[PDB]
Amino acid sequence: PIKKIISRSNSGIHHSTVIDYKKLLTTNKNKPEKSLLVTLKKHGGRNNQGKITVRHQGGRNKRKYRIIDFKRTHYDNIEATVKSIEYDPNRSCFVSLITYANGAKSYIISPDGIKVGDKILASEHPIDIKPGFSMPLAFIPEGTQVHNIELHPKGGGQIARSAGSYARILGQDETGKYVILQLLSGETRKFLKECRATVGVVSNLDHNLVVIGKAGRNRHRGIRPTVRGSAMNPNDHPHGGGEGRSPVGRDAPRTPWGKRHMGVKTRNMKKASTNLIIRNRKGEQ
Amino acid sequence: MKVILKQDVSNLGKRFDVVDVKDGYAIHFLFPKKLAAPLTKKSLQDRDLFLKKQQEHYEINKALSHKLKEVIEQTELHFSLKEHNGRPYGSIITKQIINQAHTKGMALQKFMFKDNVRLGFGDHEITLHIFEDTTAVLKVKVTPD
Amino acid sequence: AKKDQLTLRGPLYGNNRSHSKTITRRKWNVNLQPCKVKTADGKTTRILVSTRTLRTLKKHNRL
RNA sequence: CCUGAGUAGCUCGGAAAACGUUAUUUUGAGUGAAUCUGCCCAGACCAUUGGGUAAGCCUAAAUACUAAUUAGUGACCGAUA
RNA sequence: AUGAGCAGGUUGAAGGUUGAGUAACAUCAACUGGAGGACCGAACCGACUCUCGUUGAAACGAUAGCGGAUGACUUGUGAUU
RNA sequence: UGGACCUAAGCUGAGGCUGAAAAGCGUAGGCGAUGGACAACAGGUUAAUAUUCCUGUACUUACAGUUAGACUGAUGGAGUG
RNA sequence: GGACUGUUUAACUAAAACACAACUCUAUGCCAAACCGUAAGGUGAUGUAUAUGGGGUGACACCUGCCCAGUGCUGGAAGGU
RNA sequence: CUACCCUUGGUUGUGUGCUGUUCUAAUUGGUAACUGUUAUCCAGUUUCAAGACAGUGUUAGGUGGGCAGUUUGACUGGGG
């Protein structure tokens, strides 16, 4: 839960909030387990040659990525024992260290409502209905919450893997695939029942409550201060410049490039994923 | 564009002969069962030569189809599937059959089968069509480990 | 490079025009079609072919 | 039997030809003939007629020049050149 | 990415224990606490200012201050656009 | 102290891919300390050297023969680093 | 006036400017939107909508009133083209 | 009665497109498995998903100061 701390600072006030991190987790100091960690580097919006591709990225602190299993099909039908819920500095979600019943450990996603010591299973057969279990979508009745859904069959959970993410079950299609799901984006997609996912909502739904409070906390995440479009030079980004603030220019102002950013439909219907759409959050299909 | 039919009557009312659909790429170059000879030589000198070649090809096709039907009756396949006490945990495809045929030294192509992925264990008998001429019948023993 | 191995031919180099005949350097690239080569090598692969050369090889039955 | 096949050509945008694309060469794209009887050429084309039969390869001679080896000459300069 | 630095001194918070108080609170008291884009203030960063110099000692300085001076830190090594 | 040891962001890059060419993407490798394990102290000495010249005070890991016991186990994996 | 601490035209102008937590609107479902080159390819990102990006406002609490007439943006079946 | 030509109903059917099918068999994949390999590059087989779609080239539409080059008169009691 978010909370504030009286810092007694002599430089203004702050509305920053921090989560207690200990009525839900443990071990506030880095004490990980070896052979399951990969050091990750940040790019700061730069390309493979060092040229800018993304804006205002930088200042992030070093983070060691935890080796998570996303495909989860490497070893199935072996029951795992939940051993810990570890903070993941690489993502808004948290990782979970589980121990298999054969003598191995792994990292998985942490949904909300799980406990340390529980037992889970990832198989291609129907299994116990607990948040975390994964099975073919044809075996799951409607009315549940699912996350970490893959688009590639046996590809690995990519869609809906941030904190406080879920999907609403909207029935199944005749063809044995194209299960209808309402996603947390305003869209509604027909996925593949061959593709699997981890049921349950992702933990940390309170991510909408945390407050950065100051520019410093934001910079250390990896978000750099950036200038507004109006304050840009008449040549770098021609929405202003010179003495005195001026009203914005032509209708539907531009990005650093000539594109619109308020009402332009930037998705095209010339892909196979177009047939996978039911609701497009701007009408139908 | 090729204008010579080969290996069969092309799925519609016709005689197994030269005449073809006016595409040259209808199924010709996409089917290994559609062969031909250069039309430059097939103006008038190759008429009887290709007639006798077609007759000889028909005869050997019948003979080798029967010989392969007899051979598959003694080369019964044997495979395994790692499963959760019979619960589906493995995949059965034509690929392992292709690999064992490879190791045997003989060739089995895509057109000798009509499946994509299969399933099943125990000892079971299958019957797959090859042409209107013959139809392959085989037996396979899959162990559900 | 934008060219097939049979004839290493790239785009043709011309000058674009308009209603007012505006000078503009321009290139017309080739309509290269990718197809599998049918031959005896050990394992067949996919190569690019020019459509006119494709017609020539089909009319000579080059597989 | 044959004398150089996606060949000459036709159509959409061009490039070279004195030409800013027309007789002539080619095509980025598509289509696509013919057989010495025939084919191409004869600044649109065509009749007759004239020439040659394209659609594979090569070649010294007359082709410019000096990093220079050397001999010779400068209405060439003479340490501001 | 690999490292270093912040002399010295203030300061008494959140948090947890205990007690008074209260049904439990709130409110207070003692204890760990030294947290804090916390403070003063060396070195250090910068130049917001006064003066001087203005073919200067210096192609931008001396100068007394100044804000920061445990972090929106500074610097070091190499690459980097 | 730097190499005959290894790695850092990263570079190059056998082969392979992209692009008229040049050249770029790009794998194994091969490089890449500013890091990591990495075996000596004191005193005397010259116009000019010092954990390096000299005196005493410890040795080091390789390589052999020699003495005795003993079976050892990586290139693979783990801990550690 | 700017909430604040802070960045800033090196060597004329340090802040009502910029940034800023946060609010708000919107595009974006993975080979994401998007960006870079042309292309492979790469970032976004070794990320997955509570995330990225852009526009506006810029402690704190409250409101932000009339309007789609023209333009932008979206959807569109009738008719002309 | 037989005949040249029709409007109008069914009517037979060719030659083309408009969509609705089905399939892969060309094609694509930054799905997965195996192999080179040991190598998340790349390549080959299978697989998965589409699939004659997409994408590319040809020719043209629509938007298109992101980007390129242009044009921006004279007299004028300075000039506007």
Image (cartoon, coloured by chain):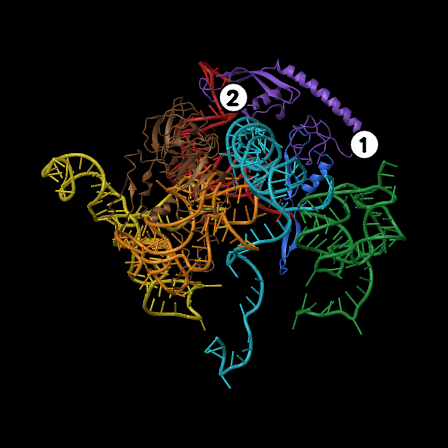
Chain colours: A brown, B purple, C blue, D green, E yellow, F red, G orange, H cyan
Mark number for residue B44? 1
Instruction: Measure how far apart labels 2 and 1 are at the Cα level.
Output: 52 Å
Mark number for residue A209? none
> Is the same chain shared between marks 2 and 1?
yes
A61 left or right, relative to A14: right
Would residue A53 be visible to someone looking at this image? Answer: no
Residue visible at 45% across and 46% down in the picture: A45
Identify the amino acid type marked 1.
Leu
Parent chain of label 1: B
Where residue G21 sits: x, y (%)?
33, 48
Who is closer to the viewer here, G13 or G66? G66
Q: How many marks?
A: 2
Where residue A273 sits: x, y (%)?
49, 39
Who is closer to the viewer here, H72 or F81? H72
Identify the amino acid type marked 2.
Leu
Where residue B74 sits: x, y (%)?
62, 13
Who is closer to the viewer here, B91 or G14? B91
Residue visible at 67% across and 32% down in the picture: B28
Of the residues tagged 2 and 1, which is closer to the observer? 1
H79 left or right, relative to D64: left
Q: Is residue D54 above or below residue A238?
A: above
Q: Secondary structure at mark 1?
A: loop
Quarter of the rendering containing residue B65: top right
Q: Secondary structure at mark 2?
A: loop
- In this figure, which residue is indicated by the disc labeled 2? B119
Q: Is residue B124 above or below residue B20?
A: above
Callout 2–callout 1 Cβ contact below 8 Å:
no
Would residue A84 be visible to someone looking at this image? Answer: yes
